[PDB]
Amino acid sequence: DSVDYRKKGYVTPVKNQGQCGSCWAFSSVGALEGQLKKKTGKLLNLSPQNLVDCVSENDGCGGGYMTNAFQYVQKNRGIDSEDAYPYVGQEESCMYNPTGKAAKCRGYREIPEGNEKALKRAVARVGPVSVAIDASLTSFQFYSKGVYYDESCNSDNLNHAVLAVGYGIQKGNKHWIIKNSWGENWGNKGYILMARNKNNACGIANLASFPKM
Ligand SMILES: CC[C@H](NC(=O)c1ccc(OCc2ccccn2)c(C(F)(F)F)c1Cl)C(=O)C(N)=O
């Protein structure tokens, strides 16, 4: 009925992505970080710069997809830690060094499109899932408290990557616990509670995936 992975050690502190369109990269390492806690008990910050700089299927600071980062981490035979490959908030030449590898992955799985009960099962059974939402409405961006629900939110306008780190219910309203990449000043300490079982509100279950480890 309720899980919150922040209290379980599956979630690293809230990051600020800056003036680079790298939410996909942050969502991607968050999912990876969760599977490393589950698989090995330890986790550390993995490297979003590594992904922006080296995932050429993507547009670097100009945008990208999580599954693509997951494919890269597999074909590359790893991703560096943050400590090895720090975040500069802009693209440069790929400078992946194998000596700083901190995660590998065996592929990924995608949540069946639109299926919120499948996303709850994934979140319960796997852990933090990378998700895509419509994050363009002004009401999203100025969120501070409660459970977000805006019927103008468009499931056919997926534009931003976040990371589902739990689910539950606040004063009667069913929600997802969502982790953003806009600083611990955004939202409620960097997090947003989004509407759950309110018809795939904002597209939350439309392009969701996790890495295999
Ligand atoms: C550039 C800003 C950036 N968004 C993306 O990198 C991005 C762009 C398009 C997009 O999806 C476009 C799409 C999805 C499905 C069908 C057709 N088109 C997706 C996502 F969420 F769906 F995975 C993301 Cl992350 C992000 O929000 C930020 N850094 O702040």
Image (spheres, rainbow, N blue to C red):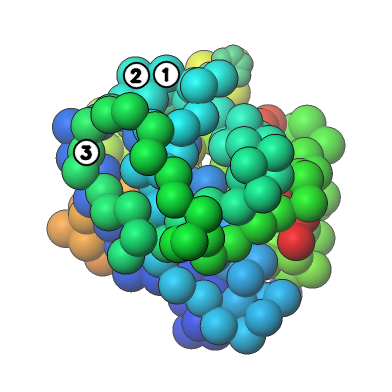
- Residue 109 relative to residue 36: left or right: right
The image position of residue 15, as x and y in percent, is 28, 57
Q: Quadrant of residue 82?
A: bottom left
Query: Is there a contact, CB below 8 Å, between mark 1 and mark 2?
Result: yes
Label 3 CB-ligand 1 distance < 8 A: no
In front: 212, or 147? 212
Give the mark nearest the N terminus, 3 or 2: 2
Residue 195: give its label: none
In front: 178, or 108? 108
- Mark 3 highlights which residue? 89
Dot 1 alpha-carbon crowd within 10 angstroms: few under 14, some 14 to 19, many 20 or more: some
Instruction: Name the element at disc 3.
Output: loop
Dot 2 alpha-carbon crowd within 10 angstroms: few under 14, some 14 to 19, many 20 or more: few
Q: CA distance from mark 3 to mark 1?
A: 13 Å
Instruction: Name the element at disc 1.
Output: loop
- Mark 2 highlights which residue? 62
- Residue 208 relative to residue 173: left or right: right
Q: How many marks?
A: 3
Q: CA distance from mark 1 to mark 2?
A: 5 Å
Specify the amino acid type for callout 2: Gly
The image position of residue 121, as x and y in percent, is 80, 60
Specify the amino acid type for callout 1: Asp
Image quadrant where one finds the C terminus: bottom right
Would residue 159 be seen by someone viewing this image from the given angle?
A: no
- Mark 1 highlights which residue? 59
On screen, residue 79 above or below 184:
above
Specify the amino acid type for callout 3: Gly
Task: Name the residue at 79% across, 68% down.
Answer: 125
